[PDB]
Amino acid sequence: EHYKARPGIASVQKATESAELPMKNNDEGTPDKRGNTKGALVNEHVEARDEADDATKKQAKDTEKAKAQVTYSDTGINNANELSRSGNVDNEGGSNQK
Amino acid sequence: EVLLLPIDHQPANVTTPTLDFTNELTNWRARVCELMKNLVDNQRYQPGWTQSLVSSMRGTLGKLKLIKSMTPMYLQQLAPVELAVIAPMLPFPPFQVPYVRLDRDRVPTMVGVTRQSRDTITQPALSLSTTNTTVGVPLALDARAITVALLSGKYPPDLVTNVWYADAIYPMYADTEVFSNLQRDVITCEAVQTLV
Amino acid sequence: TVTSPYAPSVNRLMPYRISNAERQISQIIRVMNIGNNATVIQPVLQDISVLLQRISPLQIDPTIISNTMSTVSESTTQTLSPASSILGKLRPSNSDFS
Amino acid sequence: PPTASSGHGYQCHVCSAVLFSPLDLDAHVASHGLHGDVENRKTAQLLHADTPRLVTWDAGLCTSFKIVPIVPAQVPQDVLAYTFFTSSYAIQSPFPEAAVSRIVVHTRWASNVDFDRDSSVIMAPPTENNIHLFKQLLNTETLSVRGANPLMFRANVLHMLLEFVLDNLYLNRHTGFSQDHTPFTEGANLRSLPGPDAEKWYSIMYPTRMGTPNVSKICNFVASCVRNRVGRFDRAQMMNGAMSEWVDVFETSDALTVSIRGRWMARLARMNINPTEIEWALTECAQGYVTVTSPYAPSVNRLMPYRISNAERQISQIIRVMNIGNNATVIQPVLQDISVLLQRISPLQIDPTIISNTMSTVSESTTQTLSPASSILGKLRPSNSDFSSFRVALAGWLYNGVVTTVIDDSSYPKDGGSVTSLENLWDFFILALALPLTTDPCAPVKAFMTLANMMVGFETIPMDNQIYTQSRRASAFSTPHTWPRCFMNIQLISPIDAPILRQWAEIIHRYWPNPSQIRYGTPNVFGSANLFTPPEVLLLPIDHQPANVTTPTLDFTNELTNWRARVCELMKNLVDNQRYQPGWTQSLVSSMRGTLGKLKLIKSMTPMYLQQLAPVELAVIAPMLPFPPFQVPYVRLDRDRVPTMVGVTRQSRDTITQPALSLSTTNTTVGVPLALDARAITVALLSGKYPPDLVTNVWYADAIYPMYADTEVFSNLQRDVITCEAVQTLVTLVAQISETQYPVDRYLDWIPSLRASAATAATFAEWVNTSMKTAFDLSDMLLEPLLSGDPRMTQLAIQYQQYNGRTFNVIPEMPGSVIADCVQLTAEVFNHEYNLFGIARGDIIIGRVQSTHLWSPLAPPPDLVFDRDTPGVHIFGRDCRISFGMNGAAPMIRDETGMMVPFEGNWIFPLALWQMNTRYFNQQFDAWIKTGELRIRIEMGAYPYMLHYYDPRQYANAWNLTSAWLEEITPTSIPSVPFMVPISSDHDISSAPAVQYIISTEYNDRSLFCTNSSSPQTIAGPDKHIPVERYNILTNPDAPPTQIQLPEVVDLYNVVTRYAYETPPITAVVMGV
Amino acid sequence: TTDPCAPVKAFMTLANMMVGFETIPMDNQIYTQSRRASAFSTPHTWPRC
Amino acid sequence: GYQCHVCSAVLFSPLDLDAHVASHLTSSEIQRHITEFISSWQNHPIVQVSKTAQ
């Protein structure tokens, strides 16, 4: 061994392992085996605000700090005409309370 | 072929003046410092500053304008090459909408995906990315952090770009999974046409 | 630069040649995926952030600003010193640049 | 605050009583005895800048090149008996006796200085490791002890060369002589030297005084020399049997450090002064209040390196104001110290009791709500003394260039008051009386505006906008842009609707104090410190008529009394007007009239001080300052000529080069305000008396004489010398590596180097800074205000801006610099003599040589070399791939012409290609290098080298050393290059084959000195005699002395001068009376 | 930042900063120069000045 | 130990002495009238700040 890696070969290796990570599934709102949706009985205007707050919370957990610098919830612009995918509505357009 | 960046680039140089005005970032910082200096100049816009702080103000703003910070030089030369290197290795290859400087008419506001054909008519099933105030999902930032990172930052004093990126880019390519994704996209496209 | 030296064969085989269209449709699947969800995008963005942090030759310290602004020893008897004001406003104690 | 704490402790010796607290135990015993932080670092740097150690003396000799034995000569052998030799008979030898001997560099190694400098170049002989002095700067990314990055070679050589120059800053001090008694030298004097021994050193110093027995190379060289050129031959002495002034000696010394110390001696002797002009300059600075005296007799040629030009003072002044830009806490202790010093000197004494003793005689009626005597004594509350703010406000006159004394808001009457408000009237008088002593330019517009802020609704005058209206607080007017133009164009005031405001401005415009001036110091011995003013002259806000008589006594014929009288006259009109108040009853009214009558009568010697005396104290103290003055032109009552800023630059902005073109857009604005109290200034003006009898010549003689024991200004001069020398050394040495704007001559570029940057050039700058501070024993901060910016494109200038936009600027010319001169000279002589520092030019060739020849690898025959324009040579480079062979066919390589060629023929590599693929080539080339005739020449310009010797009578092989080297080449670093060189013999020896791989390209064997040093001749080896081209004086009788052929050799022997001067304290020579 | 109306927000921040000394011509009666720059997030709100 | 000059009181802190002297003009009846004025106006809900009803 003579040549040290000048940026650090394993230190790049861990970071590119982390950057390798594939695309996370988002399967809610889609029909299951039987024909039902796979969501949580939440309408989307609370659902997307909920998952945005949870993504900011996971971002703060990923950082060492307690309050996250980059945030996704209450950024400064409003998001009232917004709706994500979840399992309130079926494919047909009605309420999946049954 | 091209990677749309909101900043002008430059070939890879290391030796150049820290005070360069060809650099758009350093030009922008120097001229904004000069404008706020011009705001302070005559004291007229503010009463209540009972001491004459204009000398100390112009001093600290000029001391800010003359600074060692090589971050604008990094963002001009080195960073676009790094993004061009990283970009083919991604599990989610980049998805870009055109940047405009100041035209009102060429600003994109809505991105949507249609499922139907061009010839038929049906009820408008708008894709869910459209239901956003901006073009996409928002993302707040820390302007303090942006400013201090732009305002301070330097190089290792042994920097050879060929040696550095030769040691650096090599284990990154050792974790390439581009080829598996190229096998994957076949299955995706075949599944789409079988579905229709 | 790379090279991959090899022997003249015929029955060698690696299936990898695709067209533009499959990449385009896989992009349209992966962007329909996002589904107006914030949790779905942030691991990719955070991991490429860490990858930029580990690939960058540019390191950042706030002590350049601290050594330039030679205004220290903040007395409580203050005359609203603007150099110390911007030092307290920029906060060079932090080292978070995510 | 004067109080008393309830203490513990009871005993008193005299009167035998016990008491309450120690805090008055001590006072009771006294009655018995009567009756019967980087800011702190730079602040203390300004207050006591540590002086350098310039003048340092060398006993012994000046030589940086020693001759070192490498392999020992045989004392026994069969072919020649031992009686031929000289080591048998133990006769000392001038040059080292050995079989092979080389010369190497090593700093002083024969010196007896009093003060060392931790700055040295100690190079081992080239048989062992010598890489550790070529990695001292940037190689903190190399594991290998035996490794070094090639791109740092030029920077390392330049830093080591700066160390080599920086060490030889001494002067060859005289010791003494002794007349010979042996007939070796016919009657020639021999020079002694101190130290523990003196035996071998005489034979070391003087070669040709040895004997000549035999046909050895040593004695054969010495026998063909010139006889008389040894020892003392010239001198100069004045007094009867005293110390000789200087001599010249014929000793061994290389011409390099003789030239270094000669140019240093001349540079130092430029700064010499003599006690007569010391006496003249000190008397002129004292203005004849204190005389001193120099002797009038033939001296002993004293040495006092003190005179400099004005450029050094100006440049160091720029650097110091650039250091202290925008803090105010550096400048606060300076003003406090000048305040303490002037408080010690000044002849007056302040007592507030004159105010009480007068104002207890004003008329009254005791049945009123108020009568103004208690109000003036309450608002003036003069019970404390604590008058240091007066001296602070005085000494800000020296430094309107950096500090602006203003008045705090607490001395302003709380967002205005009423004219019928009595306490607000008194606050108006306190303020408007205190205002003519500060240095702020908006002081007169504050002086006007306080009255208009006071009266609102009584009389209204046209203002400027809706923002800075009449009811604006008066402290906001502190820029010349915010002057209400009704104050300038006084006809805009309604002359019949606002009479009291019209005539107040008439008092201002006529009677606000006009600036004047006075001279100080001299530019004869020390320099001219100012730059925005003409030299020698001092700017002051108030007219200064000199004293007619030396016994002062009170009169009222001056500007401050006239000012006080007109202010009192306006307040008399203000109480006299029938519209403002008839509302006060006649007792209180007439009491006001009487109070103002006594107030316009009041006696004080303080305006006589500020008119006739106080600039004389200022002109006396202004030469003896650690912080010399820095002023702007004072102007009253002008929109135009008021300055708005002052700023310093550090570097050039763009590709533009000339600082006159690059200045105004790129500076660092310097300046602080400084708050003060007005009523302290007011009472210090109002109540100041003298001693009851006094004469000025006696008073200032005793008051000024004791501060003339210092040497502090003469220390500051040397400090500024080293400051300006180090900044020119910085710009030259950074110009050597980076593309800068100054005209230099880049020498060492055959050495490859790093494509530099701002961080790398800044790094190299602070290595230079650590070297310069390690020299001369300076621990305080120096060159850091330029290290903060960019070192690459520096410039030094300053300007202030007039309010219209006119820009006066000063660009001082950088003077000559002998450290930079000596560095350029040593770089030139290193370019022509590079082998001594362990460097070989050109490159190497790798290939097998099986032969029985004995040629030296540092001087190869030209058959074994090839270059770019050699027929049948493949030149490689960037696009280089290795295609493997198959089925026995040869693997091949990519040419830069795109061709493919087998592993044969003469090849040329850049070193960077080998470094980038240093692993993958080793499993491809080495088997063809060891056996096949594949021959590779790797160009790298410069490298340190390693020597290995062998007996030629046996077998030798170099593949272990070369395999070690080819393996240990790293992309970052390389190891030193080994060589297999034979050993010269003297008799006929048997030949044996040897196998060599690493050959040099051109001649690099300049470091050799002599071969075998004993025999009549050297047979079958690399042979070279003692170099006659060095000893020019011994071998050329036509050549006169003081003749050096320095730009190619060093000659190892010349004449050198030797001084015996003396460096005394100033009080040891010149004293007062 | 990738926000397209960032120059408009940079102008409007100083425009809001200078409420009291310097004014601009305005579009309708509804808005005010003293408007916070957070609202100008979409190009249909850009001022013709 | 720090002692003020009016009222001869002694304290241990100079800031306490300065506040004490600040707690410590014109006629005694005028001070009487301004004290009774400020005491008359000290707690009115003009200077003071900070299920039904159809």
Image (spheres, rainbow, N blue to C red):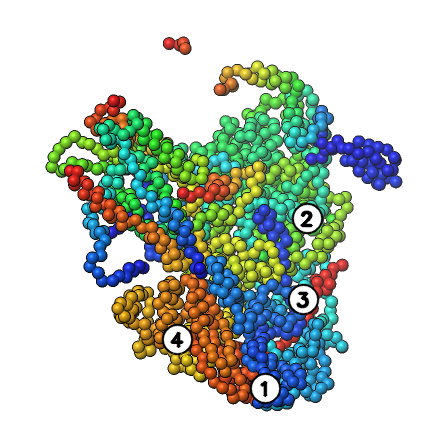
Residue D328 in the figure: left or right of residue D847: right
Mark 1 or mark 2: name the one nearer the start of the chain. 1
As helix, strand or loop, the secondary structure at mark 1 comes to loop
Proximity of marks 4 and 1: CB atoms separated by less than 8 Å = no
Mark 2 or mark 4: name the one nearer the start of the chain. 2
Mark 2 residue type: Leu
Mark 1 residue type: Gln
10 Å neighbourhood of mark 3: few (<14), some, or many (≥20)? few
Q: Are marks 3 and 2 on the same chain?
A: yes
Mark 3 or mark 4: name the one nearer the start of the chain. 3
As helix, strand or loop, the secondary structure at mark 2 comes to helix
**What residue is at 38 percent from the left and 56 percent from the top?**
B167
Q: How far apart are labels 2 and 4 at the CA level?
A: 81 Å
10 Å neighbourhood of mark 1: few (<14), some, or many (≥20)? few
Residue that carries the numbered disc 4 in the rendered image:
D847
Mark 4 residue type: Gly
Residue A32 in the figure: left or right of residue D847: left
Residue E17 % position (x, y): 40, 36
Q: Which mark is residue A7?
A: none
Determine if residue D844 is in view.
Answer: yes
As helix, strand or loop, the secondary structure at mark 4 comes to strand
**What residue is at 57 percent from the left and 68 percent from the top?**
D122
Residue that carries the numbered disc 3 in the rendered image:
D114
Q: Is D652 in front, or is D611?
A: D652
Q: Quadrant of residue D598?
A: top right
Residue that carries the numbered disc 1 in the rendered image:
D77
Question: Residue A95, relative to residue D783: is it above or below?
Answer: above
Q: How far apart are labels 4 and 1 at the CA level?
A: 36 Å
Mark 3 residue type: Asp
Q: Is D444 in front, or is D704?
A: D704
